[PDB]
Image (cartoon, coloured by chain):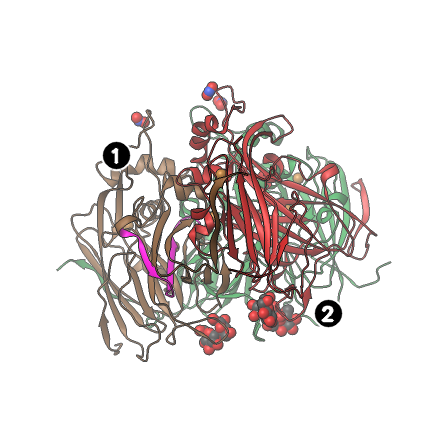
Chain colours: A green, B red, C brown
Amino acid sequence: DLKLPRQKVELVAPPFVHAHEQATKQGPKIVEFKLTIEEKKVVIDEKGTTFQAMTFNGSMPGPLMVVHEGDYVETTLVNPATNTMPHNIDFHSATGALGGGALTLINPGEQVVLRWKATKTGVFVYHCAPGGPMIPWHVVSGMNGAVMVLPRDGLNDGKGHALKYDKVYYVGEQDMYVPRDEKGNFKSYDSPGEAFTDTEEMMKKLIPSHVVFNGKVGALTGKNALTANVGENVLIVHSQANRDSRPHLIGGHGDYVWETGKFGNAPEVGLETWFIRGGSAGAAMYKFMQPGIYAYVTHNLIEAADLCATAHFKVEGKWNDDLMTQVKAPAEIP
Amino acid sequence: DLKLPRQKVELVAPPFVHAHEQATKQGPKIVEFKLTIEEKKVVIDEKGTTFQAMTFNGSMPGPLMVVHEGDYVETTLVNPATNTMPHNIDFHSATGALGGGALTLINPGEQVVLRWKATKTGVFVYHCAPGGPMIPWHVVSGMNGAVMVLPRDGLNDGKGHALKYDKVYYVGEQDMYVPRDEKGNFKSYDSPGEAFTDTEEMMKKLIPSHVVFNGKVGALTGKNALTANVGENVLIVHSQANRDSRPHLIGGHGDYVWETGKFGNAPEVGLETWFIRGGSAGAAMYKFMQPGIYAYVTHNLIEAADLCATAHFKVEGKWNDDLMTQVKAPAEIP
Amino acid sequence: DLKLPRQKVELVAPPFVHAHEQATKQGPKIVEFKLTIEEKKVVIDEKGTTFQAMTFNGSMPGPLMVVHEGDYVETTLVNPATNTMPHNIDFHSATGALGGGALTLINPGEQVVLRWKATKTGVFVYHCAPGGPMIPWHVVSGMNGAVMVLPRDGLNDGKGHALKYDKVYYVGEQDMYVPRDEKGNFKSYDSPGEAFTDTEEMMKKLIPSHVVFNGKVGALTGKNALTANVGENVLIVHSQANRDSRPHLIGGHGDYVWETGKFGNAPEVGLETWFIRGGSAGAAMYKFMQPGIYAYVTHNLIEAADLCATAHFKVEGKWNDDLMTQVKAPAEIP
Ligand SMILES: OC[C@H]1O[C@@](CO)(O[C@H]2O[C@H](CO)[C@@H](O)[C@H](O)[C@H]2O)[C@@H](O)[C@@H]1O
Ligand SMILES: OC[C@H]1O[C@@](CO)(O[C@H]2O[C@H](CO)[C@@H](O)[C@H](O)[C@H]2O)[C@@H](O)[C@@H]1O
Ligand SMILES: OC[C@H]1O[C@@](CO)(O[C@H]2O[C@H](CO)[C@@H](O)[C@H](O)[C@H]2O)[C@@H](O)[C@@H]1O
Ligand SMILES: O=N[O-]
Ligand SMILES: O=N[O-]
Ligand SMILES: O=N[O-]
Ligand SMILES: [Cu+2]
Ligand SMILES: [Cu+2]
Ligand SMILES: [Cu+2]
Ligand SMILES: [Cu+2]
Ligand SMILES: [Cu+2]
Ligand SMILES: [Cu+2]
């Protein structure tokens, strides 16, 4: 019935983002994505704590899907028979049927195909929402990601100037609720079903045990640090499907920030810390001016340093002494 | 002394709103409202948990009061002798005397009349504030509502285009603190005074037991779902007098949103989730494009699904397959 | 190497702010500040609870530093030998080296001199950040303040009109984590090092025991109330280095508010309550219209009334009956 060209997208694991154009001369197309649900026990910290995760495509967050305004997004959702629970998908970018959730419920062994038109620009959460108390449980178990709907002319600053990024990263923040036993050690479970009772009791007290980026403490540090060069404009897309976050780039700024994540609104300029409302994604762009290590954190510093919510950037380039200099190194007080 | 025409308003229970004009050719008037305090034990969940509520006009939230910029709002506050405590009222829309709280303290058996000029447009909280530790207790017991001060020319989009709503609903979100006994069951009390000690201990730990719309789990579901039709522009006013909230219309958007609630500022466009700061009201308008059920939630999904914060909309009209379609129904994986 | 005029600033204790110009015809200069770290046991409430504080210049918050865009800020940080721990400083206003933290780590007995160029306007947090789990601990122990970077032409409303304040106050909000013993009394400790284990356990549960302005319950009340006169435009700078806050002036408004704190963005108008994201500072200006007492609170009313987060303003001038009047004093119900 709908006769537009079709384009397949090969999704990639976060924090990377599949190849895409910013400004395009393509007209609308049907863009085809596939997500396969995987339920799996994973390690979430350096002490070896385990967690019953539920994921789109094996990752937390699920992959970033990128399209342009007026595209039709056609998603094949697959729930293999090796899973134990029904799942679905709700796109905050979509209109009707609970974001698609009412049309995508699939038992283990089934798949479904949903199409929605991308009428609203910005970055948006997607997540599983199977019904009732299951909705929060599936989301905080890892079943969330994001989709970016770009204007066809790319991003702008709201004063008529183009904003082009040199690279984009997707940082998905996940609040996790891992119960402790009487001795005070984290509990491990054999199945998501068995984790449910204890996990729900903890969830309703609203305090996470862990808050992590990309699924694990230290995921985006060391070999897996984010990278840039002095002079590069980097877009950081940040989502949180359940709980607020307050991103901050230590040693940098948000030069242009859409904290509510929606490109019909002009970005704010020159922020120190921005706010991602639980159930939303936002985006910040920064042109790096200095080399060295930066940390990207939520600026609840207890969550950042003690609960897991810290990423690093390693930046190459030349140090600018005009911007900052150590006038006198540490020395004994006169 | 002040010689303007007087107009009486018959308040209605939320989520409905008394009849009013958007744009008006009336000039300023003295608009007269009456609020009668009622203290009462109420049921707040489907399990039969009870709660010592304190309310304006018998409802949680108190009713929405609607006026226009430059009107004088004259409120008669009544504290009948059947109540046990002093009460007052603080309007965030008003200027001076702690929002009127310093001029409205009334013991059981008394009434008072306050007038304030509506110099600031937007939606604003009102709440009881009797002094000291009583202030939070009365507010989280249900003594809060909102008032909407419209521009005389009605709402606009900040680019010169009128925004007219077809209907308005008021959703008041209430964080409730109900203590549990040693067995882990919710406690019941014979009076608000007796609930005070246990309730205050719990309040200071900052985690609610319930978060509800319109006073009870499921208040705005079933027979009492909100309603609309495809093509209707609906304004949703949302208040939270004590704690943040992150409203989201599942399957829709906020087409025009004043998250800080104040109409001197242009609305933001095309939001997925917005943020209501504790101690404020905000407003979002959406033109429905699809029929069916929508849920309106705070997008802390634990609060929404497990603690009570979910409303429904039932929308009539024709399904738009261009916006969304199930391409292939659930079927066995090839 | 850098040959600009030098200007020394004598810092003053909050909530006051050192003398400065708004709009200036001075060009860039090197502005020189000195901060001396002090670790000390302090009383934080009227019951006599003690707390192991760590401070810049002996105060919580540290003093407000005021400069203009394009100034170079040269800070001497001193860690006297009477202290027990290493410390450093991170300015959110600065670019590179973790905001200066990577260049300013000093042991007891040492000092360091850092210079950074003020390229971004607004109000910004500064705080200690010595590494790892120490980062949150030093911040919630009191090691944070703010710096205001003004445009050279002073503030404006984003529609071409100047906004000039008659006075400025700095309100620093501090979340404190004081553990309790088995009887339920607050614990006291002999050193910050000894407070660390118990304090960290409590911090990771994310619920503060106290939330205070200017370091103590009631700090900004009584003799130490903030003051103004009817007709005065007052700027209130508010910071929170770790946790969100929702400032509200009871009986007033935010006439012009930069909630994200950055003067490259136009202020919002006519707010009731605004939001300071943890890890940021914001600023609100209000022209007082009515005399009397006002309270300035975070509008989580439990935090304000029960945990310590309330300041007062005493305002002199003539009462305006047009804005508000008690039409009928409290009287028996007919
Ligand atoms: O950045 C969005 C912001 O910019 C304005 C112009 O100030 O509109 C720009 O962006 C629109 C959406 O991308 C474009 O269609 C428009 O052509 C462009 O000027 C604002 O209207 C908008 O809020
Ligand atoms: O939506 C408010 C926003 O729109 C602007 C114009 O961009 O002003 C409009 O609204 C004012 C308040 O309602 C009107 O008085 C004005 O006439 C109208 O243009 C902005 O100034 C304002 O922030
Ligand atoms: O208040 C900042 C806001 O105002 C605008 C004009 O609408 O720019 C003003 O402020 C700039 C920064 O101070 C000035 O450089 C400019 O000259 C002045 O018009 C907006 O661009 C800005 O976002
Ligand atoms: O050991 N179980 O709580
Ligand atoms: O049974 N009372 O806690
Ligand atoms: O008495 N100590 O927990
Ligand atoms: Cu699922
Ligand atoms: Cu959702
Ligand atoms: Cu009351
Ligand atoms: Cu209030
Ligand atoms: Cu320190
Ligand atoms: Cu910081």
The residue lying toward the viewer, choosing from B169 and C263, is B169
Q: Chain of mark 1?
A: C
Q: Quadrant of the C terminus of chain B?
A: top right
Residue C18 in percent (x, y) is at 26, 64
Look at the image and tell me whether residue C260 can be seen.
Answer: yes
**Secondary structure of the residue carrying numbered label 2:** loop
Q: Looking at the image, can residue C278 be seen? A: no
Distance of mark 2 from mark 1, alpha carbons?
68 Å
- Left or right placement of residue C259 versus residue A111 in this view: left
Q: Which residue is mark 1?
A: C188
What residue is at 45 percent from the left and 53 percent from the top?
A: C277
- Please tell me which residue lies in front, A223 or C276: C276
Kindly identify the amino acid type of the residue bearing the numbered disc 1. Answer: Ser
Does B220 appear in magenta?
no
Q: Is residue C26 above or below residue B150?
A: below
In what element is the residue under mark 1? loop
**Residue sitting at 31 percent across and 35 percent down?**
C197
Give, as a single range, the part of the protein colored magenta. C224-245
Q: Which amino acid, by three-letter code, is at mark 2?
A: Gln
Dividing the picture into quadrants, the one containing residue B271 is: bottom right
Residue at the image position 19 percent from the left and 47 percent from the top: C83
Reply above or below: A205 against B239: above
Near mark 2 (Cα within 10 A), the count class, few <14, some 14-19 or many ≥20, is few
Residue assigned mark 2: A26
The number of numbered badges drawn on the structure is 2
Q: Residue furthest left?
A: A334
Left or right of B89: which side holds C304? Answer: left
Q: Position of residue C267 (x, y in %)?
A: 48, 65
User: Looking at the image, which is closer to me, C77 or C305?
Assistant: C305
| C-beta proximity under 8 Å, tags 2 and 1 | no
Q: Nearer the viewer, mark 2 or mark 1?
A: 1
